[PDB]
Length: 604
Ligand SMILES: [Zn+2]
Image (cartoon, rainbow, N blue to C red; front, top):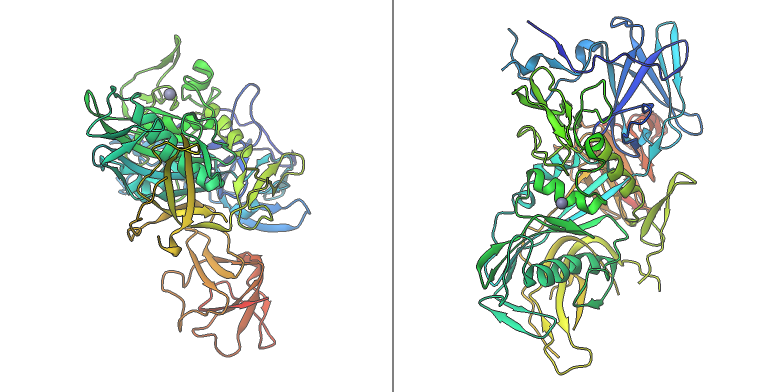
């Protein structure tokens, strides 16, 4: 017994030409080239590596399939030679050993595949697919904004020590696992040092010690709101926006211009004991008890503009291929599909408001993460969003501005009319960061502007990545590099504060020059006036790389160890591997610098 195919649906042609083929892309999920009538699916997100699935209407698993990609200007981007149906990526339930029958599962039969680089996924992209003498064109590809998510993590102890159970924050792989489920180009997970509050001061001017006089719970308690949410979370969000002061009561003062969320763990001593907070999110905040699984995907989901049971059954239940709201996930690092069903054969149906989705070969179909869904396996510790929710999440990111160090305003926002990221003016009067994603010391507390009395500065909060600038609530970001009716001596920041970047690597700064791994996105940066050691670090040597040079900088590369034999190539701006292969060197010849061995960063 062998081969159990998920998608047995009749392929519909998506091309204009000789070749009849169905086309699918795959980022945070498998998405169609042409969505069916009444189906809600996300479209391609700009600047994110995409799988390309080609299913010829008239099957041919033998004749080589090729893809020629062209940009808006009709310049050939590249040519790919697809993998035969036999080489189609497996499920994450597959095991290595040739004769636990999940290994039989395969997405579909007769599907050809390739990987389209991130820099191709930009509005204007057109494909020409050829299968021998046959050819077809896909020239109406919808590509959305390169969406961004900035997520802060802090563990708050309120009249107690921090819980120390923020699994997500302590696990880099979880940041990566979550990135696979959402339709963004870039995700930054910023670590804040845990906050310990032995005393708690309220905007009413009431100092607490020992316990909050009211009751607390999962969704309640005064501290949970005033401190956990407004002071800490909206404090971190507001400081990054440059707002020096806001009211000590309320959430409306938060501008929420960028998709910036401050996720926390909060527990405090109340008049009914130590109460752990959780189960909520919105307006740039996340109150998490469980930081992995459904609670994370739901709470964060709320920040994307989502409610509960989005669009009833049609929108909330994961479906088989003959239906709408049907898809499978994609793990772009593992190079494997994430099926929308549990690995166990329980023969259970998935129902909502009486409607049901029948199981796939015994496997129970999942659930949106705003309708009580849960991860399928430890392969991805997060809940898969249904195509309907994923489409809403995508629209949400596209409509948000982005912190952008290369922008004249420090911000960029998508122009749906010109199909490009354009500068966005942030208003406090114009407000622009002096420093971008630098370590930060977030100073926080309350002050009485009229006086008489009770102004209180809280202990300094320390972040790995933030933005710096030149009763009421104060929230100011100071660069940690500086070293730090009330006065308080500020403790220096602890050591190991680190942020994570998933997807698109961060851009090179003004007087900086990088080479970046096409695979991992891990950068090797040097400032202007600096060179590498004798040879580049072992990790980057032999790797497929792109150059990212700052406005005031120039990148010098050699294909030899030490910038030797005058075999130096000059790279300015953003240069891709294909444009690193025939570059004129200082020694008057054209050389390949696609696998460099030494580097130097100069001005100009
Ligand atoms: Zn909810």
